[PDB]
Image 1 (cartoon, rainbow over the protein chains, first blue to last red):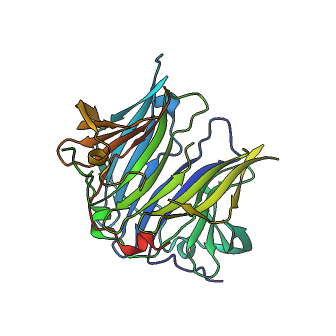
Image 2 (image 1 turned 90 degrees about the vertical axis):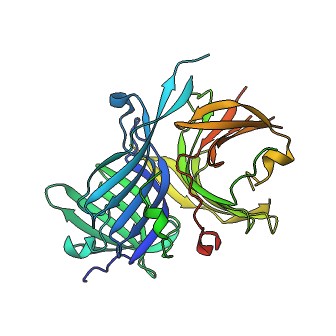
Length: 186
Length: 169
């Protein structure tokens, strides 16, 4: 009845997409690391969603967001289409730094946002508890955790019946994350 | 002689095609290579039926076997939705980049090309395939396999120790 905490540290491959899948929508993958003891996270992957229309390229990014220091660092690579007898050409962008307020998935998100248990469902071939909460003024979210281990399996941001982003975590590990993962330098 | 690859390295990767056809996918994931343990791992949407495949592969050259965890993402109509379905784990015969490729396959130093903002030594060797190494640190920057070719870029190689748990599968 009181939602659980997320694991103290976890990392996983992720798969990121949308419901419904609209023509422009992308299905992407990457890897992410969350260390709530250090209060730092890292996400590496093609950014989803990313407007190629507005920018002229598709972005690959590695972001290290340190909520303890309140700073983020982003390594960025642009992949643009070049008309040729068509090619993709990589173009590194400047690293970007700036402020960082909180981790993308806070360890206590279900407790602090008042999540309710919506039941159990099969997610990624596993028995999962579904925890539904409101992001105030923003919309609903549902986080699916493995029923036995309590590790994240699927984050749904929005409602699947109208428009939601989905992120799946197929191989969560609670192993120690070495300092170097969070070094925040290419 | 050509250089050896780093004893251990891991990196995000971005995979695509040259030329990029309209139905070609741009994908990303993460990979780890530890040649002392003779093992590698690669996690991402597979590049290149009714589904797109995410896979984590742990390829063990000390044993001669690869292990694959697989999740299928198929399209279903209702509009269109992805339907996630795990598949059986799979094993078979079996590194995608061995440590000694350049010196074992008599690679030829073509000039320095700038790859991912870095001066890169191009080493071409026997379709065919070609490996670009950072000319300073010796770390992989781009692998070109194959007039169609698969490209895989490595924007943030780290040479840090890789924990056992990474390869535990």
